Each structure stands twice: as structure tokens, then as C-alpha cells.
Amino acid sequence: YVKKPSYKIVPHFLGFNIPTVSKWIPIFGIWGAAAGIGALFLIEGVPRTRQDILSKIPIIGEHWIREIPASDNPF
Amino acid sequence: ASLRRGYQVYKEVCAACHSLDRIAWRNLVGVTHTTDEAKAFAEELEYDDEPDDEG
């Protein structure tokens, strides 16, 4: 015979609990990647982005190492 | 190549009477001339400087 139902209250805050949030952790990850890729794409033209980030990527990085010949540069 | 030849016609014929005031020497560079050729053309001319120390 059972006298009482068996349950606990899980900690919660602003209507969130850990079981639920944990399901969304990976999704925040992918959104973070999406935001990272998007941000980096937006500043791909900035010379510092190329110098510090993009030109350092293996294989691919040579796409961003481009020199104007000194004969063609007024400045 | 035609642009470079046309500059030579401008310089030797038209420039006696006509200005080309909106074009700077740097504009020729990498279009018709190298940096060195255009610097040489610029350096042959005299331009007004800022006044000296006595004004």
C-alpha cells in the first residue's frame, strides 16, 4: 500500500530548470557558432581580421596573403 | 596601352592649351605608369610650398 505520491521539486528560476536548460545547451552552442561565423564573415574585409585571423588558417590562409606590387602602389 | 599612348598625346599636344586639373600624378600609377615613372614626372615640376620662416 502507498500512502503518498513520490516526488520532489527541482530547483527553478524564472520558469527554467536544469533538465530543460540542459536540452538547450547544444543549441546555444550552434547559435554561437552561427554568430561567430557570421561576425567573422562581416569583418572579413577588415585588414586586421585577415592579418591576425584569416591568413593563419592552414592551407586556406593563403587566400588572404595578397601584396600590391610596389610599382603599382602610389602610397 | 592605348591609355598610356593617349597620355603622351595629351602631354605633347593638348597640354599646351588645356588643363587636366582633376587628375593627380598618383592617378596614373598602375593605370598607365609605374610609381617611379609618375614620381619622375611629378619631381620635374615646381609647386608652391608653405612660406619659409621669414614668411
Image (cartoon, coloured by chain):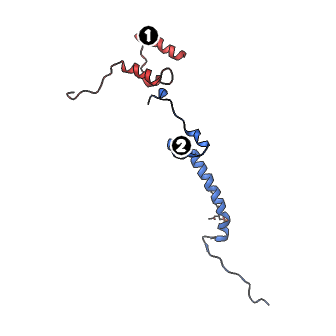
Q: Quadrant of the C terminus of chain B?
A: top left
**Label 1: chain?**
B
* Secondary element type, mark 1: helix
Image quadrant assignment for residue A24: bottom right
Looking at the image, the residue that sits furthest to the front is A59
Tag of residue A50: 2
**Label 2: chain?**
A
Q: Residues within 10 Å of mark 1 (few under 14, many from 20)?
A: few
Point out residue A31 in the picture as x, y percentages from the top left corner.
Answer: 63, 56
Query: Is residue B24 visible from the viewing direction of this image?
Result: no
Q: Residues within 10 Å of mark 2 (few under 14, many from 20)?
A: some
Query: Is residue A10 visible from the viewing direction of this image?
Result: yes
Question: Against B6, is A60 above or below?
Answer: below
Which amino acid type corresponds to the residue marked 2 in the rendered image? Arg
* Secondary element type, mark 2: helix
Image quadrant assignment for residue A28: bottom right
Question: Against A71, is A2 above or below?
Answer: below
Label 1 sits on residue:
B12
Direction from residue A67 to residue A19 in the image, left or right: right
Shown colour of chain A: blue
Tag of residue A63: none
Which amino acid type corresponds to the residue marked 1 in the rendered image? Glu
Nearer to us in this view, B14 or A30:
A30
Question: Against A62, is B3 above or below?
Answer: above
Point out residue A56 in the picture as x, y percentages from the top left corner.
Answer: 55, 45
Point out residue B25 in the picture as x, y percentages from the top left corner.
Answer: 43, 23
Nearer to us in this view, A62 or B39:
A62
Q: Nearer the viewer, mark 2 or mark 1?
A: 2
**How far, Cα to Cα, is label 2 from label 1?**
45 Å
Shown colour of chain B: red
